[PDB]
Image 1 (cartoon, rainbow, N blue to C red):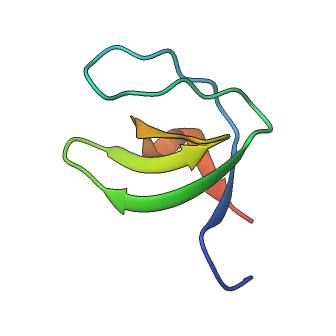
Image 2 (image 1 turned 60 degrees about the vertical axis):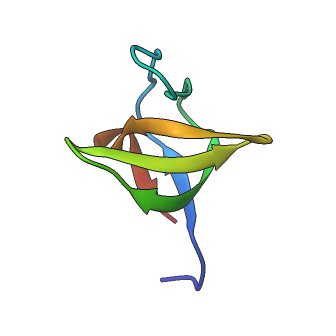
Length: 59
C-alpha cells in the first residue's frame, strides 16, 4: 500500500460512451471516484473520464 490514488492500467480501453477516456497498458491512472456499471473515473495525462474498473490496479 502507498497513500493516495495511484493505479496502473493493466488493460487497454477504447471509449464507447460519453465521457469515457482511452487507456493503454502501463499508463499511470489517478482514480477519483466510482460510477455505475463497473466504471470508475480517473485522470491520465491531464484528461479525466470513465473506464471499466477492471482495466486498472493499485500501485
